[PDB]
Image (cartoon, rainbow, N blue to C red):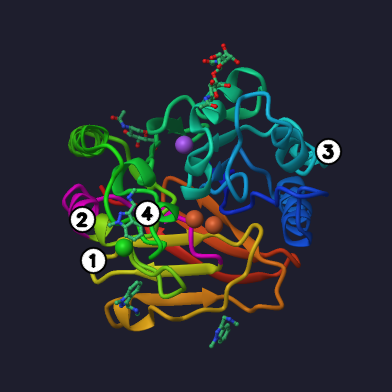
Amino acid sequence: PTPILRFVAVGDWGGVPNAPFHTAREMANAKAIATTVKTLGADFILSLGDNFYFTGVHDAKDKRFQETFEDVFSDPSLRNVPWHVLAGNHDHLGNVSAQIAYSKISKRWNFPSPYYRLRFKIPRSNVSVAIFMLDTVTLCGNSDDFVSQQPERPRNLALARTQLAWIKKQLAAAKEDYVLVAGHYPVWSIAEHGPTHCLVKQLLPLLTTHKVTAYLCGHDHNLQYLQDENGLGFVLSGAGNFMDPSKKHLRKVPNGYLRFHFGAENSLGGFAYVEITPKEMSVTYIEASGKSLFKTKLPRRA
Ligand SMILES: *[C@@H]1O[C@H](CO)[C@@H](O[C@@H]2O[C@H](CO)[C@@H](O)[C@H](O)[C@H]2NC(C)=O)[C@H](O)[C@H]1NC(C)=O
Ligand SMILES: *[C@@H]1O[C@H](CO)[C@@H](O)[C@H](O)[C@H]1NC(C)=O
Ligand SMILES: CNCc1nn(C)c2ccccc12
Ligand SMILES: CNCc1nn(C)c2ccccc12
Ligand SMILES: CNCc1nn(C)c2ccccc12
Ligand SMILES: [Cl-]
Ligand SMILES: [Fe+3]
Ligand SMILES: [Fe+3]
Ligand code: NA
C-alpha cells in the first residue's frame, strides 16, 4: 500500500453547560466522525479549541469532561483514538490548567501544556510530520474579555512574547517533511470573526518564511479552505457544535484566497479529514450528514 497518516480535525464542539450538555450538532458530528474512523481510519483526532461552552471547566474533576466529551465521543470505533487538544477563548474564561491536568485522568486526552510540538512518522516510511499546537488566546488575548469579542491584547505580555519566540525558534529549526501549525483563532476567515490581526501580523510571516504546509484553526463556526498565492493552506474546521452562515468578513480576506466555504444555517456542521502520504497532504471536508463537501491536495515540498 501507500504509507499514510490520517487524522480528524474538529473545532468548537464543546456542547452546552445546561442539560443534556451537548447539542444535536455535537452528537451528529460525534456519530459522523465515528463513521469516518470506522470506514477510513484515524491515527488521532485534533481539537481546534472551544472544548467546553461557554466558560470551560473549573477543575480537572469537572463533570463536563464526561458529560460533554467522554460520553459524547463514545461510539465503538472512536473509543481508543487519541485526541490532541488546544484551547480556545471560551476554555480560557474557565480553567485551562484543568484541561491540561485532565491528560493524566483520561488516556485518550492529550494536552500537556498550552502550546507544544507533535512529531509523527508516516508508518512504513521515513517521511515525518510536525504539528505545532498553539495557544492563540495567551498569544493574542481572550476575545471574550472584550465587548468587541476580538482579541485586542494579551493578558500577559511575557507569556505572549515567550510563545512567539518559541514558534519562531521551532519553525526555523524544523526539519520535518511536513509542518502543520494549529491554533484556535484564524489567520484568514471570511466569516463572523474574520481574520485575527494578531496572527496576520505576527504568525503569518513565520508560516511563509519557514515553508509551513498549512495552518489549521476553528473559532469561526463553519468550514473553510483558503490558500494564498504561495500555496500556503488554511484549513478552518470550527463546525462541531454551531453553524454560522455569516460572510461579514469576506472583503477582509485578499481576493482569490477563499477556495471553499460551507456555512448553511440548517446544516448540522462537520469536520475535516486529513491524509498525509509521502507524496501529498489531502484535506477532505465532511458534513455531519456524512457527505464530502470539498477535497483538495497540498504537495510535499523537498
Ligand atoms: C484549575 O484546575 C486545577 C486542576 O484541577 C486546580 O488545581 C487543583 O487545585 C486544588 C488545590 O489547589 C486540588 O484540586 C489539586 O491539588 C490541584 N491540582 C493540580 C493539578 O494542581 C486549580 O485549583 C484550578 N484553579 C482554579 C482557579 O479553579
Ligand atoms: C528515505 O526513504 C526513502 C524511501 O523511498 C528513500 O528514497 C530515501 O533514500 C530515504 N532517505 C534517506 C535514507 O536519507
Ligand atoms: C480587561 N480589559 C478589558 C477591556 N479593556 N478595554 C479597553 C476594553 C474595551 C471594551 C471591552 C473590554 C475592554
Ligand atoms: C468586515 N468587517 C471589518 C471590521 N471593521 N470593523 C470596524 C470591525 C470591528 C470588529 C470586527 C470586524 C470589523
Ligand atoms: C451555504 N453556506 C455555504 C455556501 N454559500 N454559498 C454561496 C455556497 C455556494 C455553494 C455551496 C455552498 C455555499
Ligand atoms: Cl482581530
Ligand atoms: Fe467557538
Ligand atoms: Fe472561539
Ligand atoms: Na482561564
Residue 126 is at least partly visible in this image:
no
Residue at the image point whose x is 66% and y is 59% from the top: 241
The numbered mark, 1 or 3, whose residue comes first in the sequence reads 3
Quarter of the picture for ligand 6? bottom left
| Residue drawn at x 74%, y 51% as measured from the top left | 30
Q: CA distance from mark 1 to mark 3?
A: 41 Å
Earlier along the polypeptide chain: callout 4 or callout 2? 2
Q: Is residue 147 left or right of residue 59?
A: left
Three-letter amino acid code at disc 1?
Asn
- Residue 3 spot, x, y in % from top left: 52, 41
Q: Which residue is mark 3?
A: 76
Dot 1 lies on which element? loop
- Could you give the CA–CA distance between mark 4 and mark 3, rounded to whole angstroms? 30 Å
Mark 2 or mark 1, earlier in chain: 2
Q: Position of residue 220 (x, y in %)?
A: 49, 64
Q: How many marks?
A: 4
Question: Which residue lies under the disc numbered 1?
Answer: 230
Q: Tell me the magenta residue range.
A: 201-221
Tag 2–tag 1 contact (CB < 8 Å): yes
Dot 1: within a 10 Å radius of its alpha carbon, few (fewer than 14), some, or many (20 or more) residues?
few
- Separation of residues labelled 4 and 1 (CA atoms): 13 Å
* Residue 262 location, quadrant: bottom right
Provide the secondary structure element on which disc 4 rests: strand
Residue type, mark 2 in image: Thr
Q: Position of residue 84 (x, y in %)?
A: 54, 35
Q: 1 or 213: which is nearer to us?
A: 213
